[PDB]
């Protein structure tokens, strides 16, 4: 039939064509509940102090600095040295390190044994 | 309702599709006969004529879409090039796109490969 | 809130040929493909079993995505268009007048006088609108996003400064 | 398709409050009053010759403005690039190296006067 | 083209290889090879600052052109007789190159014919 | 470029949406409530909702498709959205 | 060199006794004048270092850093005007005393003629910086900031102390000129590589390389606005001077020993650039870009090439100028918003037309675009590293690939777009700020027009 | 912006397409034909091809000079 | 010329090519929900443009005049010389 759309982590299946999003059980219709209520009350705060002439200054939610903390400082205290963590941390802590070191020393020794007898040319490269 | 822009667009479309004696003649036309002449990559050779065909294609696409003849636009008609300075600038570049194609092609000192004879096809 | 069957099919109809006009370009071709009988929507209005309604929705909504352009029509002011957020460069919040200086304050004098008594109206309205919104707010955090009106005379609606003093769409 | 007395009241009241606000945004006749500044008497004379605005006066002020643009922007730059060039640039060597013009068999030279012999026998391939 | 069809599409050897052409002695049926007369001179065209790409045998008709081109200003419609002589020389050199190509082409068909009738004659 | 004055979009709404010949003009009005004042539901609104927005040079919000029903509502939304204040 | 040092030392009682509100004025004026006296030192005779006495000498390597520090002292001086207008008069004079002592110790370090004196004043910089960071900080983590900075710098420095006293015992002197003239080949003995490590790791500590770069991000974030530019500006470059002078004895052992750290910089300058695409704080953003630039200058040092040395010498000055340049902007936006979140306030050009212009050439200088001295300093390093090991251009191209992706990203997410609707206290930019970035950016191009002065001592 | 616009809009009618901007457009329209066809008359050779294609498989064996085809 | 609004009753479907598609939907058994707001966009005032080549042939009869003027120019140049 018509080409069926499949979801992807980068290109998610659009909201219309998921099977279950049209299969909403009444439990889900209640489950959305009054999230609009608490959202609209948060609006009520925002528009209140914004429209308040007495207030004059920066107004910020806990939501932003929660993410700031959890992206900057909350990492280590909740960090556990899992086997996976140690594995991939060592992986890119000595893989690129030793790999760049290897390729660089490889080419450096290449020129080292290309210059001691004079294979490599240094004719115009005076301004080394 | 867009006559001056129409003529300018048509002649520009013909120019980018190698209009003889125009800018196109001493342009992609020359480069195409050169690539057909010179020892060039085959796939590049077929590709550049496909490119010329597509160059004709979309250049006439804007032609038969914009100036097709079926009005589709807001009820207030604003399509009008009545600004004198717009006309002056458009014609200033227009004369070059008509003239300057050859007001430099033969005036320049002989600088390229002068392949005169070649297979008719 | 919850988008109902009526709303779903209305959005599908809106998005179906907005789209299909871009498919056909010409208005004669438009009118034909739109009159590819419009009763194609109304030929099966008798769907008392909503399960068959949902199945024909699985056909309707999940036939549009491939009968629609990979590069569909967008308007300039429409999101993803040409002039959706073009003029946001020139728009400035209303509070950017208090920082002005006596040279500029007296060099547009009466404009700042009118702003003065407009913000005076804001002063006289703030307490009235907050006391009006608190008394009629149901417990648990309102009930919808509907904002209460001004039920009295001479009073002001709750939370009225921002949606009025918002910058014009053509600030230049 | 559910427009309750609440938000029609809200909406048209916001509408004509903003309408009144914009009616107060109308700058009064005195606005947008600017302060006195300094105007140049020569340009004052030129402007006073354009209030009548005869075509010849318009053209005359046009060419005078083009003339002051030229003097400040055409030969004023060549006043000092030439001074820098033929007295300071060319004062240091190898600064302005010019490609030798194409000397030609059959052209004489201004200083020496000698002519290089013209090209030898052509194939004479007539068309 | 016929040449690509014979070589690329058909037998590659049967038609001249562009990267190889020519691979043959110059007097291939051409006894007493009087090489083309020197009319172009390297010193003159170096003096004329010609491009090395156009420093071919036709150079004689190029250098002369510049002479008139040096003495034609202000005019771009001048210098026609010697420039048409150069155009005819480019014609004769393009027919020279392609006729040398067809010369070694029929000589390559001669190569196959020759090595098939004098070696495979057994 | 016009300011699209209240009279400008006002004329727009007496040509568009008074374009509707399915209902005879005698019962047509600027306050016309098409669902029962004209007997045709918001269904036979959405299509011309898409037509008129193609003319004014604007996009009606898809969220605001419903309830946007009478010519008075048309001038309402056009005036507030297009800052039609003159 | 008494000519410039004595005015700085004796300037201290002026600030410590002047009237409660003329102290700012007098400190500023006298800082500009001793900087005026300082720029007279740009002169460098032939190849001889400009000698002054048995203990004080300078050269073309030193002079740009000296006049740098003298030029900065007014910069954080009048940047402190906003942040210290509400604290006690005696604390104000103490803060000015801290800044003046810091500048004094810097000009003492850079003019040092013998090694151990350079070292004493090299560690004498922590005390003013530690005091400034800990006392006049703003947030809570400033205490751990001071701990990290002080402990890192010391744990680096002490091996250098032991190494230097060992050099004095063995060679016979620690004077710069003699050890350059009486230099001997540092052989490949198994004690010699630890000698090299002791003489190098100390400077590497206050030149944050990959791995050992936590003190700068965790200190500059909440350092006082005046102090932060001083840390990011000069004390990362006194270590560079340390390498510049100590590498005369570390050869030829530096030829192959530098390899672990060398690559640790190149891949390093990518990671701290790769980390630099994603920061929740603008101050951390500038700090990580700074770390990338110092990894660049590190690989500039370790090749031991005259072009590498020129690229370095330009790079310390250019990076310090641009880093402090950006840190001033971060201070200004934070002070107006009283927070340091990244995407808290985008589209500030709609409110401060000239401030985002300042942002624009600040980022452009961070880009290292030609003909700015940032580009020329980078470019000399490009050439030297190419002549070193061919491929190095791939990694360094990734660095000149990430730098602008984060620099212009910071523009688009701070100045471009639109203001966030909640904030409404952003007033018009005060002339103090825009004036200070004017005095920051205009000489950045002025000395660009004359690159010989900061080009290097090998000219 | 203000009233009395030059192309002041009659509702859904031609917005006074000035015939002056028409006649200059036709000047350049005649000029494009000028440049395509009086150049053709001046020198058709440019789009004619000067000299012809000397098809290789039509020539004689002397100028080509094969060694004797019998040999 | 301030907003010369015309009558609506004049700009209906009749005569316009939209009547043909109106016949088409007449085959479908329907009436055009909007087929009148565009009657101007079917009348000859803005519709019925010249063909795409016809647009390309913008005054090509003046080009045919150029034929004769150029040919006669060269002809009198050669005739009198
Ligand atoms: C050419 C390419 C495609 C081009 C695009 C045109 C073709 C689209 C093809 C779609 C095929 C599909 O099988 C049919 C569909 O979409 S059926 C949607 C309605 N399905 C129902 O079951 C409605 C039941 N009834 C109600 O929900 C209310 O009565 C109503 C909302 C109508 C009142 O509205 P009023 O505004 O109050």
Image (cartoon, coloured by chain):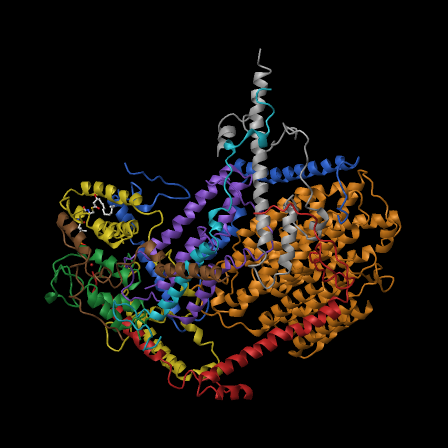
Chain colours: A blue, B purple, C yellow, D red, F green, G orange, H cyan, I brown
The percent coordinates of residue D39 (x first, y second) are: 53, 86
The percent coordinates of residue B48 (x first, y second) are: 47, 43
Which picture quadrant has residue H4?
A: bottom left
Compared with F56, G284 (above or below) is: above
Q: Residue at x 70, y 55 (%)?
A: D104
Compared with F81, E22 (above or below) is: above
Compared with G58, A100 (above or below) is: above
Q: Nearer the viewer, residue D68 or B24?
A: B24
Mark yes or no: residue G298 visible.
Answer: no
Q: Nearer the viewer, residue D53 or G275?
A: D53
Q: Nearer the viewer, residue C15 or A28?
A: C15
Mark yes or no: residue B35 visible.
Answer: yes
The percent coordinates of residue E100 (x first, y second) are: 59, 34
Is residue A59 found left or right of G146 in the rendered image? Answer: left
The percent coordinates of residue G391 (x first, y second) are: 66, 42
Is residue C37 found left or right of G76 in the rendered image? Answer: left
Quadrant for the N terminus of chain G in the image:
bottom right
Which picture quadrant has residue G31?
A: bottom right
Is residue G316 found left or right of B65 in the rendered image? Answer: right
Q: Residue at x 20, y 68 (%)?
A: F14
């Amino acid at each position: 039939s018509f080409p069926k759309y499949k979801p992807s982590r980068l290109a998610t299946l659009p909201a219309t064509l998921d099977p279950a999003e049209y299969d909403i059980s009444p439990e889900t219709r209640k489950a959305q509940a009054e999230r609009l209520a608490i959202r609209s009350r948060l609006k009520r705060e925002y528009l209140l102090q914004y429209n308040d002439p007495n207030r004059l200054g920066v107004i910020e939610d806990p939501a932003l600095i929660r993410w700031t903390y959890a992206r900057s400082a909350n990492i280590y205290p909740n960090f556990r040295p899992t086997p996976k963590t140690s594995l991939l941390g060592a992986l890119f802590g000595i893989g690129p390190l030793f790999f760049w070191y290897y390729v660089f020393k490889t080419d450096r020794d290449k020129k080292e044994k290309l210059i001691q007898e004079g294979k490599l040319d240094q004719t115009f490269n005076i301004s080394y | 309702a867009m006559p001056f822009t129409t003529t300018a667009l048509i002649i520009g479309s013909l120019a980018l599709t190698g209009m003889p004696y125009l800018t196109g003649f001493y342009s992609k036309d020359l480069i195409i006969e050169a690539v057909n002449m010179s020892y060039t990559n085959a796939w590049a050779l077929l590709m550049t004529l496909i490119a010329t065909s597509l160059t004709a294609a979309y250049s006439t696409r804007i032609i038969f879409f914009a100036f097709l003849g079926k009005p589709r636009f807001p009820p207030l008609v604003l399509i009008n090039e009545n600004n004198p300075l717009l006309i002056n600038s458009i014609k200033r570049l227009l004369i070059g796109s008509i003239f300057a194609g050859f007001i430099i092609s033969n005036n320049i000192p002989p600088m390229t490969v002068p392949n005169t004879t070649m297979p008719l096809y | 809130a919850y988008l109902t069957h009526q709303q779903k099919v209305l959005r599908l109809y809106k998005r179906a040929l907005r789209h299909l006009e871009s498919w056909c370009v010409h208005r004669d071709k438009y009118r034909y493909f739109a009159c590819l009988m419009r009763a194609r929507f109304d030929e099966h209005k008798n769907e008392k079993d909503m399960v068959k309604a949902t199945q024909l929705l699985r056909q309707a909504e999940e036939e549009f995505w491939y009968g629609q352009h990979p590069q569909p029509y967008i308007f300039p002011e429409s999101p993803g268009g040409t002039s959706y957020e073009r003029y946001e460069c020139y728009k400035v919040p209303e509070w950017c007048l208090d920082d002005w200086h006596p040279s500029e304050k007296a060099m547009y004098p009466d404009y700042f006088a009118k702003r003065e008594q407009w913000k005076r109206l804001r002063r006289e309205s703030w307490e009235r609108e907050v006391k009006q919104l608190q008394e009629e707010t149901p417990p648990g955090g309102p009930r919808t996003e509907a904002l209460p009106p001004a039920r009295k005379e001479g009073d002001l609606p709750p939370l009225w400064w921002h949606i009025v003093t918002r910058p014009r769409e053509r600030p230049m | 398709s559910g427009y309750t007395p609440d938000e029609k009241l809200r909406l048209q009241q916001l509408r004509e409050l903003r309408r009144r606000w914009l009616k107060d945004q109308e700058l009064s006749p005195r606005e947008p009053v600017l302060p006195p500044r300094r105007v140049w008497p020569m340009e004052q004379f030129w402007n006073k010759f354009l209030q009548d605005g005869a075509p010849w006066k318009n053209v005359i002020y046009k060419t005078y403005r083009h003339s002051i643009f030229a003097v400040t922007h055409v030969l004023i730059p060549v006043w000092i690039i030439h001074y820098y060039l033929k007295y300071h640039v060319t004062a240091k060597p190898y600064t302005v190296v010019e490609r030798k013009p194409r000397i030609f068999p059959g052209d004489t030279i201004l200083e020496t006067g000698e002519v290089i012999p013209l090209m030898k026998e052509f194939p004479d391939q007539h068309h | 083209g016929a040449h690509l069809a014979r070589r690329y599409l058909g037998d590659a050897s049967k038609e001249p290889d562009p990267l190889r052409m020519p691979t043959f002695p110059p007097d291939y049926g051409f006894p007493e090879r009087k090489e083309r007369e020197m009319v172009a001179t390297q010193q003159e065209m170096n003096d004329a600052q010609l491009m090395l790409q156009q420093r071919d045998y036709c150079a004689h008709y190029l250098i002369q052109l510049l002479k008139c081109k040096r003495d034609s200003f202000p005019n771009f419609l001048a210098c026609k007789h010697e420039q048409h002589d150069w155009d005819y020389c480019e014609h004769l050199d393009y027919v020279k190159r392609m006729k040398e190509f067809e010369r070694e082409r029929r000589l390559l068909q001669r190569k196959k014919r020759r090595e098939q009738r004098e070696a495979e004659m057994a | 470029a016009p300011p699209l004055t209240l009279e400008a979009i006002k004329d727009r709404v007496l040509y568009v949406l008074k374009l509707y010949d399915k209902i005879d003009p005698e019962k047509l009005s600027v306050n016309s409530h098409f669902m029962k004042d004209l007997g045709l539901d918001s269904l036979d609104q959405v299509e011309i909702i898409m037509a008129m927005e193609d003319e004014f040079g604007f996009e009606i919000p898809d969220i605001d498709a419903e309830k946007l029903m009478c010519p008075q509502e048309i001038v309402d939304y056009i005036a507030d959205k297009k800052d039609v204040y003159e | 060199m008494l000519k410039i040092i004595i005015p700085t030392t004796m300037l201290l009682p002026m600030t410590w006794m002047s009237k409660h509100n003329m102290i700012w004025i007098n400190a500023t004026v006298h800082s500009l004048l001793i900087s005026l006296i300082s720029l007279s030192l740009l002169n460098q005779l032939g190849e001889n270092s400009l000698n002054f006495s048995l203990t004080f000498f300078s050269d073309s390597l030193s002079a740009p850093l000296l006049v740098l520090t003298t030029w900065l002292l007014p910069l954080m001086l009048m940047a402190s005007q906003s942040h210290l207008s509400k604290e006690t008069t005696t604390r104000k004079k103490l803060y000015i005393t801290m800044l003046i002592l810091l500048q004094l110790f810097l000009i003492m370090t850079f003019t040092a003629t013998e090694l151990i004196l350079f070292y004493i004043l090299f560690e004498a910089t922590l005390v003013p910086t530690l005091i400034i960071i800990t006392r006049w900080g703003n947030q809570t983590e400033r205490l751990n900031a001071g701990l990290y900075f002080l402990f890192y710098t010391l744990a680096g420095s002490l091996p250098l102390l032991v190494a230097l006293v060992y050099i004095q015992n063995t060679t016979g002197s620690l004077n710069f000129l003699i050890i350059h003239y009486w230099s001997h080949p540092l052989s490949n003995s198994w004690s010699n590589i630890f000698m090299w490590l002791a003489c190098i790791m100390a400077f590497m500590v206050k030149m944050p390389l990959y791995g050992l770069h936590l003190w700068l991000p965790k200190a500059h974030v909440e350092a006082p606005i005046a102090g932060s530019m001083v840390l990011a500006a000069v004390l990362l470059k006194l270590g560079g001077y340390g390498m510049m002078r100590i590498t005369t004895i570390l050869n030829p052992l530096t030829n192959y020993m530098a390899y672990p750290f060398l690559m640790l910089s190149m891949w390093g300058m990518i990671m701290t650039s790769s980390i630099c695409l994603r920061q929740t704080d603008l101050k951390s953003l500038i700090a990580y870009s700074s770390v990338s630039h110092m990894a660049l200058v590190i690989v500039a040092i370790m090749i031991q090439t005259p072009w590498s040395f020129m690229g370095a010498t330009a790079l310390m000055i250019a990076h310090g100028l641009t880093s402090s340049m950006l840190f001033c902007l971060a201070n200004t936006n934070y002070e107006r918003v009283h927070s340091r979140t990244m995407i808290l306030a985008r589209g500030l050009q709609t409110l401060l037309p000239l401030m985002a212009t300042w942002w624009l050439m600040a980022s452009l200088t961070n880009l290292a675009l030609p003909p700015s001295i940032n580009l020329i300093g980078e470019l000399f390093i490009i050439t030297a590293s190419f002549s070193w090991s061919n491929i190095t251009i791939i990694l360094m191209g990734m660095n000149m690939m990430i730098t602008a992706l984060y620099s212009l990203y910071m523009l688009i997410t701070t100045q471009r777009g639109k203001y966030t609707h909640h904030i409404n206290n952003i007033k018009a930019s005060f002339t103090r700020e825009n004036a200070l970035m004017a005095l920051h950016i205009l000489p950045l191009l002025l000395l660009t027009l004359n690159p010989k002065m900061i080009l290097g001592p090998l000219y | 912006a203000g009233g009395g616009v030059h192309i002041e809009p009659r509702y859904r009618q031609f917005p006074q397409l000035t015939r002056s901007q028409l006649i200059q457009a036709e000047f350049f329209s005649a000029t494009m034909w000028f440049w395509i066809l009086w150049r053709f008359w001046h020198d058709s050779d440019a789009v004619l091809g000067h000299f012809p294609y000397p098809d290789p498989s039509q020539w004689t064996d002397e100028e080509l000079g094969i060694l004797p085809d019998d040999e | 010329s301030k907003m010369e609004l015309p009558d609506y009753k004049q700009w209906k479907i009749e005569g316009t090519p939209l009547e043909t598609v109106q016949e088409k939907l007449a085959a479908r058994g329907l009436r055009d929900p909007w087929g009148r707001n565009e009657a101007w966009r079917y009348s000859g005032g803005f519709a019925n443009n010249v063909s795409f080549v016809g647009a390309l042939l913008k005054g090509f009869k003046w080009g045919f005049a150029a034929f004769v003027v150029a040919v006669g120019a060269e002809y009198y140049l050669e005739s009198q010389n």
